[PDB]
Amino acid sequence: MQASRARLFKEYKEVQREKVADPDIQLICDDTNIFKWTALIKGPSETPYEGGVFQLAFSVPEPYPLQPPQVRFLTKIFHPNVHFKTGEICLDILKNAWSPAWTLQSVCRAIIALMAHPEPDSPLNCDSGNLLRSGDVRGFNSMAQMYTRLAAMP
Amino acid sequence: QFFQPVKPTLGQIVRQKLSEGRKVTCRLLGVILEETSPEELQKQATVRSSVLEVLLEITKYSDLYLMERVLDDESEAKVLQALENAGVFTSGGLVKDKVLFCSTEIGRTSFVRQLEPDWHIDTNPEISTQLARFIKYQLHVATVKPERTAPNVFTSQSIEQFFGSV
């Protein structure tokens, strides 16, 4: 229990001790629950998600960093590896391939990389995945951009 | 008399045929635009003047998504400028963000299944047949009725004829 708090303190320290340009990631530790975090991530440039801001909800288990956090999109997103109705993410580092080497910040970065480089296999949105697998990249970008403009630009 | 006749407006006719279907997807070529192939969209795009009144009544009542297969980026711009030339975008109706573009015919089926409209309007029979399993109502626009349409796939010669009359 106290090991998790020490680790989460290093990460809260590092997200405060930085004013780096291009804050593509902004982790917001929570007021009263050290184990609840929210993140703001910028859509990766040169992707249909560019210009959007997506909110991620982190639910940190008490054995963290020995156990992965529970992460999901609160912003709607059209992506092969995100369940549109629930925001659940299919990413192996959040499940089987987790390691204490990962951090909340690097998890956000893996999600951004996933947004820029989808995996039409392992699909939680088969319509989004079908567009990519069938070679309809214009269609994928068109619908992903629409949802970015309608749901991820406040 | 003053008490025993009647006459409905175009909006009431359109809304009646929509049958409370307040979410609609619809292709562009042929049914809304005069052009009939993506190759033509590389040269010009033109909204059918006969579809305009009914189209606007649909946008006031229903969330509408237009979609079409195109061959390049310049075709997209030509389409958007055509829709704007005809005043298809209005406050309270259709917005430019809800006009979608793809590179394959079957890509439209992915748009529609994601959007889950009450109505889809198309001209490709394989698309209408494939979507009848998922979409409550469809209008298949064709010169002649397919020999076989699903019971929930209705056929007509134009959007304005099907929704614009009784």
Image (cartoon, rainbow, N blue to C red):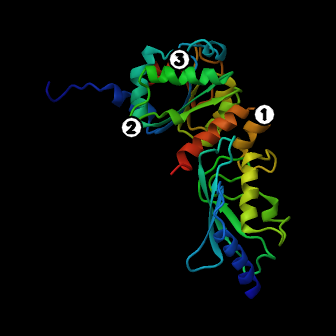
- Say which amino acid is labelled 3: Leu
Q: Identify the subunit bearing mark 2.
A: B
Task: From the top left corner, tell me how far across and down residue A55 is, in percent.
Answer: 60, 59
Query: What residue is disc 1 on?
Result: A134
- Say which amino acid is labelled 2: Gly
Residue in the foreground of this view, choosing between A30 and A119: A30
Mark 3 and mark 2, same subunit? yes
In the image, what residue occupies the spot 61% across and 40% down?
A145
Task: Determine whether B19 is above or below B86 in the image.
Answer: below
Query: What residue is disc 2 on?
Result: B92
Mark 1 and mark 2, same subunit? no
Residue in the foreground of this view, choosing between A18 and B94: A18
Task: Look at the image and tell me in which quarter the C terminus of chain B lies.
Answer: top left
Q: Secondary structure at mark 1?
A: loop
The Cα atoms of the two marked residues, 1 and 2, are separated by 35 Å
Task: From the top left corner, tell me how far across and down residue A46 is, in percent.
Answer: 69, 40
Residue B156 visible here: yes
**Number of other residues with Cα within 10 Å of mark 3, as a class: few under 14, some 14 to 19, many 20 or more:** many
In the image, what residue occupies the spot 72% across and 58% down?
A89
In the image, what residue occupies the spot 59% across and 38% down?
B135
The reply to whether the C-beta atoms of the residues labelled 3 and 2 are less than 8 Å apart is: no
Q: Identify the subunit bearing mark 3.
A: B
The Cα atoms of the two marked residues, 3 and 2, are separated by 22 Å
Query: What residue is disc 3 on?
Result: B33
Q: Secondary structure at mark 3?
A: loop
